[PDB]
Image (cartoon, grey):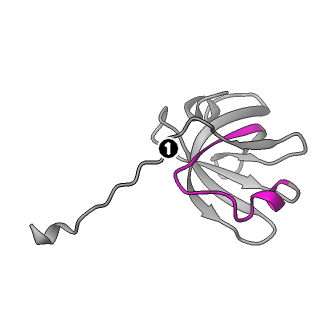
Amino acid sequence: TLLISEVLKTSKQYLSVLAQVVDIQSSDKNIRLKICDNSCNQELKVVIFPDLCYEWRDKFSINKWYYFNEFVRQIYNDEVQLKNNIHSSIKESDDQRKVITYNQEQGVF
């Protein structure tokens, strides 16, 4: 598995990345995500296409970590992103802690 910091600069065609989903857009027949690391301060755009996108439609959870396995690296507008492809696979990370915090409106203090 490569870090997003790696992904941003690698020359590989195929990669696998463990990362957090910080944005979901289910805009029809495709899922578009932003994913995030602890290696970098930048997000990475991921597009999940027909086939794969069929099972992940309503599945993704915000801030959850997943293994994106054997995705394809591409460049669009000077921006690197990853895409689904025939060999691709996605798995929820089994070692993740759900933390629930509440923030209080501060104008009260």
Figure quadrant of the N terminus = top right
Q: Is residue 41 left or right of residue 103?
A: right
Q: Name the residue carrying label 1.
A: 42
Q: Confirm whether the magenta stretch covers residue 68.
A: yes
Q: Quadrant of residue 95?
A: top right
Position in image of residue 50 (x %, y %): 86, 60
Rendered position, 107 above or below 95: below
Rendered position, 79 above or below 62: above
Classed neighbour count for the residue bearing mark 1: other residues with Cα under 10 Å, few (<14), some (14–19), many (≥20): some
Q: Is residue 104 left or right of residue 33?
A: left
Between 58 and 11, the one lying in front of the other is 58
Rendered position, 81 above or below 25: above
Which residue is painted at 54% across and 57% down in the image? 62
> Dot 1: what SS?
loop
Q: Is residue 74 left or right of residue 88?
A: left
Position in image of residue 28 (x %, y %): 77, 72
Q: Which residues are magenta?
A: 52-69
Question: How many numbered markers are drawn?
Answer: 1
Position in image of residue 109 (x %, y %): 9, 66
Q: Quadrant of residue 3?
A: top right
Between 38 and 77, the one lying in front of the other is 38
Between 16 and 95, the one lying in front of the other is 95
Q: Confirm whether the magenta stretch covers residue 67.
A: yes
Which residue is painted at 64% across and 33% down in the image? 7
Position in image of residue 73 (x %, y %): 74, 39
Rendered position, 73 above or below 77: above
Q: Is residue 52 left or right of residue 97?
A: right
Which residue is painted at 17% across and 66% down in the image? 106
Which residue is painted at 53% across and 39% down in the image? 96
Three-letter code for the amino acid on which mark 1 is drawn:
Gln
